[PDB]
Image: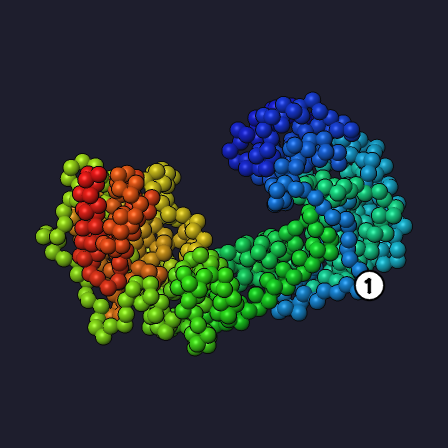
């Protein structure tokens, strides 16, 4: 196989910004310099191995010119292998082949769990010693290899009796039939093509099927031998044993390449070790819809792949689920991983269907409260409010309960259940605060340092906007880089961004954007919806650090990124001193900011903005808690006033700062610090802004008495 120089391929792979392969990652100048004249014992080059990555940027891995490539080009392949197979300290190793004691081995039938499994499949691959791969085979040695393997297959035991079908000399009639029954491979994969997999097509190639059509072998498709056991249903035990018995019989007729580092050698590094892919096609629509579906699978040792194109238009939710591991475990460990993981995932799908039967459509489905409570046990009972107030009395009382519009207690602890360092819940709608009050009320009291009071949360008290108790905290020049004040707001009559439906989002965005588009004067600006953004706008918003992304796992697992990015948007006035985030965590985050330290103008602009938005919609507000938000941490005023502060001076005193902070109830984060009021609930908006203003103005006069 003639390819370009290794050096040319490297340049091609690197200059290709669509390419994010491991080949790209590890094919360094040093690797090229080292291996550019090197041949394997079969004549292969590293260029032949990485060729396909030059022309197919979506491909993650190299291939190999022959089985000796892994040893000959070891600095390249060990790095690629350790990386892809997640090998702890690059200590690549693999145990002896062991399918287990087949006579006493038993797995439960996977359809026990909801009858969701359409079919079950286990696949192996082997390299036969003494032969190259696509780039180093000749026409004749590939045929000799084919002859060697079909001869082995023909001699197989009774259950395996069947017919060998060479590709060469096959009628176009059987070709069509055999691919229909999904028995035939074709020369239609361009990654395989550019890795030399179709040279001398179709010679040296064929398939073997047994009489029962539950045993399939492919010769020289990619590997020398690919062996597949398969049937309808979830009978993994029979599928697995039929595969294991065949390969152990074949291993007496064929010498397969194995070493104690990589296990069984294959053409693609992804199939090293056991080479074993044990899988089901299962119907798991609800599980698949979960925000962290991929993570849930990986946590159970399972790799999911969708089956789009394999069904009719209205049939969805069918996934291929397989063991994620190939290398560094036995075949028994691998099929066990698949079985245990798939069993669990299928049990979760049944629990999901059961727990969300009759829930509103488009509303985030959720795992049973008791399931999530177990996950929540990882969280600290000392720090994590979510877990602290989730007593057995609370579980007993609220399990099975929904708000009028479909929110559950399960919903609101989900973010902490999957992110055990998250300390607060995320509610589903304003009614949560009355419906789950026995949970939420003590949590709120704790977090905000308050108690149950007989009296109404005071009305919004913004103050007199023309006669404020603060002005410019830094007239001089620079201690304050910038000042910012924001509130969160919920709109009455809508579910929160956590669990709300896509249709709700659209309708909410219509209400809000309409109001934003009509803002006049200092507040006049442009609404940028995330679904229909013009390219130029996207980049400017990032450079401005205005854009929000679907990248926080806590908000993700709360449901906050469902149906992305429908209904989400950014508004800012022309000056970029007034900003609104639409439907990120709360329905709105309303923000006023500017360079310098004029808090009064920032706060004034904010309040006027809130009011002008409020003309077109009602804000969710509570007698108990003031303004209602998704997270209980931002109740009350839901207001955060902050400054970007230069205090290199007293930052070098790291504990009269914290004492200036505790004393004036401020929070600090980093001689440049983001300083803000800590309180949200139990005080007026005017006071919140004024607490930050005094705490900061005092830092500042301390900051020259150095």
- Residue at 22% of width from left, 68% of height from top? 457
Residues 142 and 443: in front is 443
What colour scheme was applied to this rendering of the protein? rainbow
Query: Considering only vertical position in the picture, is 668 above or below 412?
Result: above
To which quarter of the image does residue 560 belong?
A: bottom left
Q: How far across and down, in percent of the image, does residue 577 sit?
A: 23, 44
- Residue at 26% of width from left, 42% of height from top? 650
Query: Considering only vertical position in the picture, is 703 above or below 588?
Result: above
Q: Name the residue under label 1.
A: 103
To which quarter of the image does residue 687 belong?
A: bottom left
- Quadrant in which the N terminus is drawn: top right
Residues 77 and 495: in front is 77
- Residue at 75% of width from left, 36% of height from top? 67
Q: How far across and down, in percent of the image, does residue 382 sit?
A: 42, 63
Q: How far across and down, in percent of the image, does residue 82 sit?
A: 63, 41
Residues 355 and 212: in front is 355
Residues 184 and 625: in front is 625
Q: For the view shown, which residue lies furthest in the left direction?
A: 467
| Left or right: where 200 falls relative to 621 | right
Badge 1 element? loop
| Left or right: where 367 falls relative to 477 | right
Q: How far across and down, in percent of the image, does residue 501 sit?
A: 41, 62
To which quarter of the image does residue 461 belong?
A: bottom left
């Amino acid at each position: 196989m003639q390819v370009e120089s290794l050096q040319n391929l490297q340049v091609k792979i690197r200059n290709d910004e669509r390419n994010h392969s491991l080949t790209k990652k590890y094919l360094t100048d040093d690797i090229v310099k080292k291996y550019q004249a090197t041949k394997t014992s079969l004549g292969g080059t590293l260029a032949q191995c990485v060729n396909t990555n030059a022309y197919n940027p979506g491909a993650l891995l190299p291939r190999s010119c022959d089985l000796n490539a892994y040893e000959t080009f070891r600095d390249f392949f060990d790095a690629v292998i350790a990386d892809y197979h997640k090998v702890p300290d690059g200590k690549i190793q693999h145990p002896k082949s062991n399918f287990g004691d087949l006579k006493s081995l038993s797995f439960t039938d996977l359809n026990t769990y909801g009858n969701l499994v359409v079919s079950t499949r286990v696949r192996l691959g082997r390299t036969v010693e003494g032969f190259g791969f696509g780039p180093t085979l000749t026409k004749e040695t590939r045929i000799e290899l084919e002859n060697k393997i079909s001869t082995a297959l023909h001699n197989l035991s009774g259950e395996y009796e069947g017919t060998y079908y060479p590709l060469t000399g096959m009628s176009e009639e059987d070709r069509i039939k055999l691919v229909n029954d999904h028995f035939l491979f074709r020369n239609d994969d361009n990654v395989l093509r550019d890795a030399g997999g179709y040279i001398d097509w179709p010679t040296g190639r064929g398939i073997f099927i047994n009489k029962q059509k539950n045993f399939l072998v492919w010769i020289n498709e990619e590997d020398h031998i690919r062996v597949i056991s398969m049937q309808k249903g979830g009978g993994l035990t029979a599928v697995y044993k039929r595969l294991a018995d065949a390969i152990q019989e074949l291993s007496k007729s064929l010498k397969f390449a194995f070493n104690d580092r990589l296990g069984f050698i294959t053409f693609c590094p992804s199939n090293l070790g056991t080479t074993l892919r044990a899988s089901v096609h299962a119907k798991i629509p609800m599980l698949a819809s979960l925000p962290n579906f991929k993570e849930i699978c990986e946590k159970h040792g399972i790799q999911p792949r969708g089956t789009h194109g394999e069904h009719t238009e209205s049939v969805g939710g069918i996934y291929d689920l397989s063991n994620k591991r190939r290398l560094g475990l036995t075949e028994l460990d691998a099929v066990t991983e698949m079985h245990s993981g798939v069993r669990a995932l299928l049990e979760l799908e049944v629990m999901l269907q059961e727990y969300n039967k009759g829930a509103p459509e488009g509303v985030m489905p959720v795992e049973p409260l008791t399931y999530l409570a177990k996950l929540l046990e990882g969280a600290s009972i000392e720090k994590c409010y979510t877990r602290k107030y989730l007593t057995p009395e609370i579980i007993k009382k609220y399990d099975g309960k929904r708000t009028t519009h479909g929110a559950t207690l399960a919903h609101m602890i989900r973010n902490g259940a999957y992110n055990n360092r998250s300390i607060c819940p995320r509610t589903g709608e304003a009614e949560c605060y009355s419906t789950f009050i026995d949970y939420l009320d003590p949590l709120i009291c704790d977090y905000h340092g308050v108690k149950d009071s007989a009296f109404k949360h005071p009305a919004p008290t913004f103050g007199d906007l023309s006669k404020l108790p603060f002005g410019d905290l830094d007239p001089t020049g620079k201690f304050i880089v910038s000042t910012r004040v924001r509130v969160g707001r919920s709109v009455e009559g809508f579910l929160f961004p956590t669990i709300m439906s896509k249709t709700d989002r659209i309708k909410l965005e219509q209400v809000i954007s309409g109001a934003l588009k009509g803002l006049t004067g200092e507040h006049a600006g442009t609404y940028y919806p995330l679904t229909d953004m013009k390219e130029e706008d996207r980049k400017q918003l990032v450079e401005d650090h205005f854009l929000f992304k679907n990248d926080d796992p806590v908000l993700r697992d709360a449901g906050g990124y469902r149906d992305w990015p429908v209904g989400r948007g950014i508004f800012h006035n022309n000056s970029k001193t007034f900003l609104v985030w639409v439907c990120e965590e709360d329905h709105m985050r309303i923000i006023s900011m500017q360079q310098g330290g004029n808090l009064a103008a920032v706060y004034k602009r904010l309040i006027e903005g809130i009011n002008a938005i409020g003309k077109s919609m009602k804000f969710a507000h509570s007698d108990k808690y003031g303004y209602i938000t998704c997270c209980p941490s931002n109740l009350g005023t839901s207001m955060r006033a902050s400054v970007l502060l230069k205090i290199p001076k007293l930052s070098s005193q790291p504990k009269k700062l914290d004492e200036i902070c505790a004393k004036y109830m401020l929070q600090a984060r980093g001689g440049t610090y983001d300083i803000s009021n800590k309180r949200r609930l139990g005080l007026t908006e005017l006071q919140a802004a004024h607490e930050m203003a005094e705490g900061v103005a005092k830092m500042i006069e301390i900051e020259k008495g150095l």
